[PDB]
Image (cartoon, rainbow, N blue to C red; front, side, top):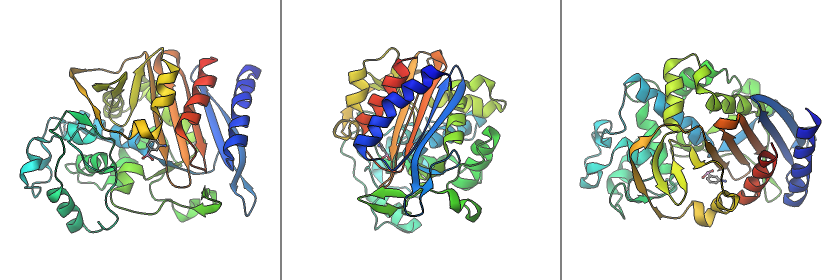
Length: 357
Ligand SMILES: *[B]([O])([O])C1=[C][C]=[C]C([N])=[C]1
């Protein structure tokens, strides 16, 4: 890396690790459309295995970007519409609530109070349906934003319906492969197990446990290299050869709703650039990010705005990730750690480094 970049990263990251007590970390800066990688520490402390560019990490919520992108591609293919009511795809979903809730609502957390999480007692397809049928909304559709896995997960389960594929095959075929994310998995195969880092929560080594709609809402595992490649793709959609994906990417970055100074895409979250750092930093905090907030509709939605600060945080019980990019400046960063540390800290660091370029 050019010394500038080096200095920046090191200057900012080291202290973060030290303070947060992060066992491993990989970072990639995308500068002028070129990535530069940094790794630190361990992937597995016990076996003293270090973090490399091949180490796999749990994306947690950053999976939502993928979901949102696979959904846009489906839209671009003419297989679904955001305006379609949910029932068109899950006709058994017969209860009165479901009435006017469309794919758009689900995909954006504005359905009217769907829970953050799917209850752990929900296992079968039967449990699921019940869960849905019996859910009672707190608000009218399209009035209040509630960050929810059961909201977005559901959208992604249904988006792939017309295709005929399972969520995983569709992601693979339609997203991973075309983009050349060969080390990106929902289910990590045996041949890759050796590179899969241990999450660490309370000194204990942990892995994401399976659950309803996990693939769809938080099930991706990937590497710093593939992450960087994913960031490059979202930064320059137009260079993507596959029409639908290209288009699909752009739709995921479209602005459907606004709250405070933030806009809701399809998995992505964006702000206007330049941005008020206090805004994003503090906004990232759980108390704020997970709360119920009133939304204003953008009618019609605004197409992907080059001047933005695009991003998404993500976490599992043993990991914590962050991605941010500014299409207009051809810059981004990706931060992967095998420890779930505080959001604002991630935000602060990303902004420091990115502000410096
Ligand atoms: B996801 O893993 O529920 C997620 C959302 C917002 C912040 C973070 N760290 C994770």
